[PDB]
Image (cartoon, rainbow, N blue to C red):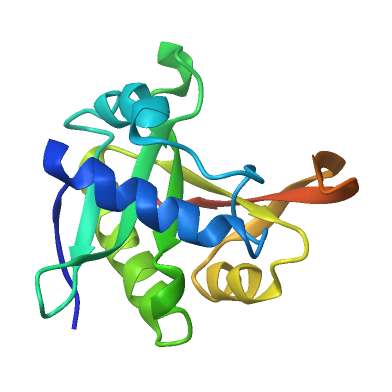
Length: 165
């Protein structure tokens, strides 16, 4: 099972570790090389009460995944628009974790005052694209080959959903 709670400083290590476990597959992150906790300390502390980072613990209390809400643009005009990022420990892939995490993210979002929620997913990540599309997200954009890794170009798709009635 999985239980969500607000992230804490001592979680940074596990959060980065999960992030790094996904780099190899080059299916969700824009990094080709593993990063260090120090390289992400800013991003980590950058979360707020309205745009938080949540971690999900397995039945053993170990952080197995996380959900991050981030600002779209540091401008009041975009205050009700946010990005949602979900990373799962590569070792937990293929267990239905994604579905549960997205559902929780969506339950939480409205209470954060978020009206429009967007997700940045690589064009070749069909599983993630299908998951979001089953939950009300539509493709709002496709930025062709703007990501380059291993000498290959990748497309970035932007999926969005308006939550507010």
